[PDB]
Image (spheres, coloured by chain):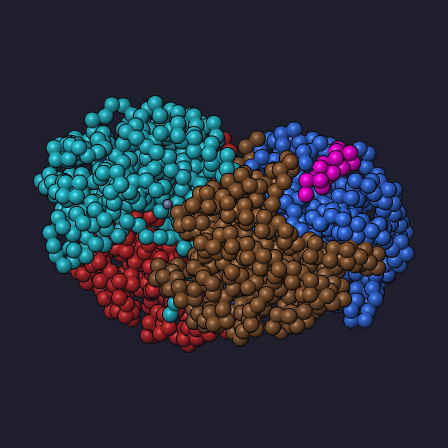
Chain colours: A red, B cyan, C brown, D blue
């Protein structure tokens, strides 16, 4: 039977993910024989995460708290919101009310809920170029048109942002939202400077726009001085945040959040129960305890954080020993490094050869771009690989490198 | 600042509930701490659930499985889908391939993913009248127009279903989907007969329609014979199921699924990673073990199920005892009883008056209807309250009843 | 074949118009023998229009101007726009650039073009209650939600308008446009007072809303003072007008216009060629010469106008002496009088009986309301019927009335 | 003020048109002194049209028929529908009922009315490549996704059509309509062979698709045998036609039609009054007399048609004589000829340089393609320019051609 006839026309806005084509082409070789170390993942290190400790909490809460197995309010258990509030004020410089927090199915869920309430099909949403592949996909399947703005070692080029806004309006285009990942961007790995952050806020006010700040990697900072979220600088209330504990507490727990105000918060809350009903009860209680027991500092700060900072150094050391000639980013936050093949080279076919020949998995990155740029780009992860995997990983990458240029 | 201006016009399709307005007046009475018995809730008894056991497996999973903290595939871990296929084939008379099942954020998430792929704004979707408010709400905020078909003690009046289709088509109206809750429907509590289930499939085939079957309460059947889901008789492949373990495993785990095929499955999977990324890793693993070691039959079939059946009889005897001259449903499945005030009576204010004067919380019901009927309806839940609360619950309900009627 | 399955879901937003249903029930009576006296349709008197003259200029234009048979720019021939600009300056307080004028397929097309550029599905658009049925229908098939505001002898109640707006925003509803017919409204026949017009402009500014002014009957005024359009008072550029020459030159020529600015004008014009290509060349050239030769004064102002004014006096005169106990409107402009049956009486039912038992055609009216009110309303037209037919008509109308009430 | 913020998101789907942009850049040249030879716009020759004749009928109609200045039923006066039905049966092998004919504002309005009832945002609509730009623009601003299918001198490559269809379905894409211009296509000027017309009908039936047949040039055929419209072969009723008399009676009268059945016809009719109200009364009556008096035979068949055929031969003679090494279409019908510059050559700049240096106007070509093809295309029209102007225009064109290549 042809089910294609029953699809909604908006289903044609839904398309495949390149980061999924290779993550499957590898899943085929990883189970059907071959052994491979990947630099393509986006997960945090499960070994750096206190699993046994989380198992203990999971075990206690399930037998201790009956609610751990039942529905939770649409915006999350009050205690998690009260704790997340204090947590943000403590470690991310955020003075936010618990009533303004909405616990979602991870940042992904937060970005989706927001798009549903803020996007009308055709609306143009401007983003960094490149940007997080999944947010672009999320927004386009909602009918949005994406317009990207170039980035550099200091993040989005705020000067190019204003020009894009003007070029768009000069065409009579309707623009409303700006989507940005200020700290440790996926996939570039760069972070917006404080100078560009204040300039961004000025531009949002100037053109009367709203900003959606993605803080997924705010707690993965290693070098930064005292860089604060745009939200902490938001005196006009033009920014909305989409956060997550996935890179901390674990990426499978599905715990994230939205910080918004006024009628936007209201509509977000209103539409939620019929969409996901509520964020997972165990996850919320596990997170509530993790925070209350002060395990953030005890395990993530003075623990997993250093573990990531290290893998970052070794991957860069490895790159700066074997590929000192090539161009790549120097992240002071996040969990990715964007490597660049010679200008012109194909990044998707090269990513294939690394598997088809050297047995190492890397993400093309090309699909992370909002236009024709980024062909020769390649994203590399260092948060999942072991200390040993990384050197061999990029060494094999360096093997095929000169083996072609 | 007026955020109203930044909203997307489709955000106007988002509206309040009733199972929210009453739950806010109850929390307002509980905030300023006042005792109250609840018959409104839709949760399974957390005490009839083997929390302790789940906790141990939660501890096991997190301790020994690193993947229980990371991203699972968008459609779920292969082992869970393979187990579900077996669990369904054994307890729900359904034969399905693991490749055709997708683990979602409960039945809710399943219904939403399905709405997003099958609904274009303006599409009419046919449902039972009354039906589950959250699905009505979920589909309407996607822009669908709801057309209801009356139900009786044998479920949806299938004959009137064809009548509605004929009426709609006579007007030139486009319809493609029928959403039905065959067993232990929420809020009516009635279950479609096998006779009507066979006719429904024929009507869907005659008008080339697709059916969305909500199996949420298929495992909460008491004094029932041998009923099988529409999907088991679906020889043309016209039905899609939206199931869940919410009532079995726990309503907070967020574990549900979609069973679709062909291009509909493809599109559903393709859009999932950018929406929820994946169902909770823990939950997925907690459910995997739970099923693999036969705890469904050990704790639910011969433990929880019997507890619910018992609470069912107590509420009915209580109703039959105190309000013999009033009308209400006699469920053979599910967790609710629909009570009817005198024809003409306002159930919404009655519920408020019952909570303000007697301290018992019940759900209006009118909001579950698709047209102007059901004004005198009141939904009653018996799966969460205690055996002691029930009698006292409907007792007080009867006092205000005879007080006015 | 069942074409229902091919329809776009938005086609479901398209619905029937009683003002064209019973109007088609009369089209059957005429072409079937029955001698009918019509007080329905809103056509101008074809005998008060210089048909012969127009016939002469039509001949001329066709033989002397080769363009009268070919396409024209999407926004209309420059000469007509320039001629309309001056015309509007001399008779309607308007100082507009010919560049800001777009020649459309009557005001109908003007309203549809604006809806397409300003309305996202779900958007709330505020209108008067009652309001012009075709415009409500036009906006809703574009997915808008209509919210009406009661009118009186002085037009829209501006005080209730601000309450509705505060009401909407309190619910978190998004609103943006206000559609008003300030002079000689269809169907009430009332005109907004200069006092309320200034207040409306204040509210639009206060809430940052746009106003679309329908000027259809600005040239069928009979006794106001220097009442000026909202657009001539629009110092903030918040109003857009949708005008037409159909009530002057002839309702069948399809000559109307949109007056807008900036990006709205840009987009309105960008989308036009692909939907209508251009307004009728022959009609544009006929209108041009009609204007250039001073026929507006010679025939409309000093001919048609007076005839219509006479027809109005006659209808009100007849309504006053044979039906003095009924309440109805007294228009100072336009071509309609809204007549009212006793509260509770059914106007739709009354309309069918009148036609069936007396051969007089009137328009129900209820269809023009935005809510449940207006059941007893009946709209009467005095522009088309001869001055001999008018008294005979309402005389019969009075008879059915009195024997019923 | 920034009106961009008030735009509907869907306003962003509206974009510029080279065809409209070039026509306006030429009208400015005509007024700005310069006198040029035009081979662009798709207008009929105003001298080959019996203007003088149409003039007296226009005068006659206006003075004798009062209905010629008033509204008409949304679908057009009954007499016209009946005459068109007879006209189609005689000169276009079409047996259609007068009830299935809807008089629209030209072929453009017909196509817009159909898109609104048949397209949901995101729907894929397949067309020829290239195709008429206004239809592509019309469907895309309605949110449609266009997929073109290559054509040759025998029209659409039906074999490539089925491969495209299989390509779309394999990706899970939803498609339902196919828009085609079988005879004398704009811009290619080629006509589908009867062999492909039957194959197209088979494919539509095989995949259950609807076909919208554009018959704009069915009456400007010169050498085809007895080619019949797909609609005359539509035994399953899968084709809907969008026709017009613009190329016969005159392109500026705005007299076109839709031929559909069942629910599609019902909905196209229900929505029509609120978008255009009705086609121009004068144009309808003028067309009614034109047909009834047999002027199609007397002035078009034995007049205009032979005149156009001559211009058709003259342009081909001039081209083959001065550009014998360039490839260009040889139309057997229509009014356009697609000229091709050498592969790689930019057609839009060439058109500007031609208009600037030689003062001859042509259309860029590239805008009519659904993909990146056509860069070197240039559309040439032979219906409007005089017998004399054509050779001069093509010579000047040849001059710049070899001056560049
Ligand atoms: C920029 C960004 N935003 C949001 C997310 C979502 O994070 P999550 O759905 O695991 O809570 C990620 C991780 N893939 C990310 O990199
Ligand atoms: C009809 C119906 N369907 C599905 C569900 C599932 O809800 P979920 O798997 O998100 O706990 C429920 C529970 N409220 C329900 O009543
Ligand atoms: C208020 C109003 N607006 C617009 C119109 C449309 O006028 P037009 O004959 O130029 O399409 C009418 C009459 N049908 C009207 O009454
Ligand atoms: C293929 C095609 N279809 C439809 C039309 C519309 O013709 P019209 O709006 O003058 O009745 C044209 C000419 N603009 C055309 O080339
Ligand atoms: Zn994109
Ligand atoms: Zn509803
Ligand atoms: Zn309405
Ligand atoms: Zn295109």
Question: Residue D298 versus residue C361: which sits nearer the camera?
Answer: C361
Q: Position of residue C338 (x, y in %)?
A: 50, 54
Q: Main secondary structure of the magenta part?
A: helix
From the viewer's perspective, is D222 left or right of D10? right
Evaluate whether residue A172 shows in this view: no
From the viewer's perspective, is C398 left or right of A311? right
Residue that protrudes farthest toward the front in the picture:
C321
Q: Position of residue B44 (x, y in %)?
A: 20, 41
- As drawn, B155 above or below A143: above
Q: Position of residue C114 (x, y in %)?
A: 56, 59
Tell me what residue is drawn at x 77 percent, y 55 percent: C52
Evaluate whether residue A183 shows in this view: yes
Q: Does residue D91 show up magenta in the picture?
A: yes
Q: Quadrant of residue A197?
A: bottom left
Q: Quadrant of the N terminus of chain B?
A: bottom left
Question: Residue B157 versus residue D39: which sits nearer the camera?
Answer: B157
- As drawn, D388 above or below A24: below
Tell me what residue is drawn at x 55 percent, y 54 percent: C318
Tell me what residue is drawn at x 36 percent, y 44 percent: B136
Which segment did they paint magenta? D77-93
Q: Quadrant of residue B380?
A: top left
Q: Quadrant of residue A344?
A: bottom right
Question: Residue C167 versus residue A327: which sits nearer the camera?
Answer: C167
Question: Residue B348 versus residue B184: which sits nearer the camera?
Answer: B348
Q: Does residue B307 show up magenta in the picture?
A: no
From the viewer's perspective, is A182 left or right of A69? right
Q: Position of residue A258 (x, y in %)?
A: 33, 60
């Amino acid at each position: 039977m042809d089910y294609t006839k029953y699809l909604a026309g908006r289903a044609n806005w839904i398309k495949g993910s390149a980061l999924a084509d290779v993550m499957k082409k590898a899943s085929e070789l990883q189970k059907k024989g071959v052994k491979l170390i990947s630099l393509a993942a986006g997960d945090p290190d499960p070994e750096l995460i206190p699993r046994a400790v989380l198992g203990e909490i999971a075990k206690e809460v399930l037998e201790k708290e009956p609610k751990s197995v039942m529905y939770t309010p649409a915006n999350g258990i009050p205690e998690l919101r009260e704790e997340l509030a204090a947590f943000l004020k403590k470690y991310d410089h955020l003075e936010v009310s618990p009533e303004n927090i909405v616990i979602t199915i991870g940042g992904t869920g937060a970005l989706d809920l927001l798009g549903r309430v803020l996007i009308d099909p055709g609306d143009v949403v401007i983003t960094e170029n490149p940007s997080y592949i999944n947010t672009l996909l999320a927004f386009e399947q909602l009918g949005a048109k994406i317009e990207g703005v170039p980035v550099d070692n200091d993040g989005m080029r705020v000067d190019l942002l204003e020009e894009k806004i003007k070029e768009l309006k000069a065409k009579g285009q309707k623009v409303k939202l700006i989507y940005t990942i200020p700290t440790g961007q996926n996939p570039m790995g760069v972070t917006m400077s404080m100078e560009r952050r204040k300039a961004l806020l000025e531009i949002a006010s100037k053109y009367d726009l709203l900003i959606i700040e993605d803080t997924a990697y705010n707690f993965m900072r290693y070098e930064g001085g005292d860089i604060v979220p745009l939200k902490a600088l938001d005196n006009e209330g033009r920014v909305i945040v989409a956060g997550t504990l996935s890179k901390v507490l674990g990426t499978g727990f599905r715990i994230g959040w939205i910080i918004a105000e006024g009628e936007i918060l209201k509509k977000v809350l209103m539409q939620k129960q019929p969409i996901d009903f509520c964020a997972p009860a165990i996850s919320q209680y596990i997170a509530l305890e993790y925070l209350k027991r002060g395990y953030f500092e005890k395990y993530h700060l003075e623990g997993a954080l250093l573990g990531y900072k290290e893998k970052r150094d070794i991957m860069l050391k490895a790159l700066e020993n074997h590929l000192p000639n090539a161009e790549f980013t120097k992240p002071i936050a996040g969990m990715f490094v964007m490597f660049f093949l010679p200008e012109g080279a194909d990044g998707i076919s090269f990513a294939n050869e690394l598997m088809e020949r050297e047995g190492v998995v890397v993400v093309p990155g090309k699909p992370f771009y909002t236009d024709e740029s980024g062909k020769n780009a390649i994203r590399l992860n260092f948060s999942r690989p072991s200390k040993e995997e990384i050197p061999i990983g990029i060494k094999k990458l360096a093997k095929l490198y000169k083996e072609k240029f």
